[PDB]
Length: 304
Ligand SMILES: [Co+2]
Ligand SMILES: [Co+2]
Ligand SMILES: [K+]
Image (tube, rainbow, N blue to C red; front, side):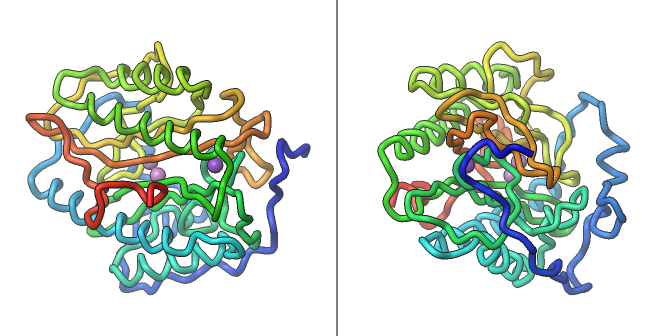
């Protein structure tokens, strides 16, 4: 394998961390290849659930708990801390909130969150590399509680970073918020990509194509698929009661991605940096509710 950048995996990984059996488990947690019956059952469908009031309560709770866990990780971002240490804290925080860490054994993913440093676009595996000053790092948290999944992510600065890093992170968040601001009944899921790409282009950044936002509730990833790039073919129309994520991945260089031999880590083919932000959204009559919103601050962590 020829690596695309300066980053390398730092193995071995610590033994898989246990989840006490009192925590309720999604189907894939105990499947030997980490496959999910329920997701596959509905794979290939365009149909989009309309959540009940019970579903909404469930989605509100788990999305709030997920935000709390993301906030735990945010407080640990500093030079010298390894992504594995962050994942340990995250794993414990999920447990402490009576949630299962959704990534854990999802298609045999070996950790409890994804940490994506620099040229890692998404799905990085927490490992023994200490974070380095100048790094940008995204931590993506998904929790599962009472049958529902909640999903959010943010990119962070590791001490002082260069102007390029500042601009890429800022613009990515701005891409996210502009998309969210367009969400309400009757808007085509395919429109968000035009908004996202138009802002990214304008700042000289490109937009990852192979990964998208998604529906989420009782399944972790389901309809709708939601691309973040312009002129896309996504299918469907927003409606009050839909829940989905928007999670744009934006890059300094080109848009093309490839996967490390670990089968997960998605990196820029050119080795340039990528940043991402993500919220789980509920479409309401007037617009949408940001279920994974930060409660103790108007702003993401990187703005402090
Ligand atoms: Co996510
Ligand atoms: Co997501
Ligand atoms: K990254």
